[PDB]
Length: 220
Image (cartoon, rainbow, N blue to C red; front, side, top):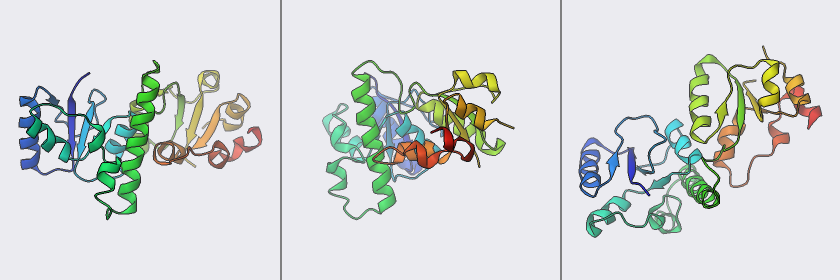
């Protein structure tokens, strides 16, 4: 049990003060902007749909309201996290006015934290994409970001998209070359990239039929 924080959407003075506090209590703060899988807790000023937030959800981190740290300060130790989760009733029944997007991001973070924890309590490693073996066929501009998000949820991303890799893959995601029909014939889930984020965000998992790539539909 570890206390490794990253901070998001807070101002510099808040970050300085919170870093000081976290360190005094025996925690660590990872200062780099990019999501770091070694963190355990992220304190978020206001939930935004971005790579860092999505990766935190894929990894099942505590995604916390800053009132968590104020409670730690008072207590003089790291307190129980559940009542400070952005998606907890304790926060959401008090911030009844936040917009629908932030509510959605909050709930998704709490839901995956709980689900991943429940699975980890049963010896399943990693996060939302645990056991996925993924072939990625996307635009060079989007490639690194998709890889990082998948890896943050515990997916292995395979090198390239050659036919021999189909026998190793569970999933193939493509931007709307690569032989999709053959991958589908070899029972790979051949899906639009929107599936990845929708798997993280949706209360009930996206259904493969709706995300299936055109050449793979008959193989469902």
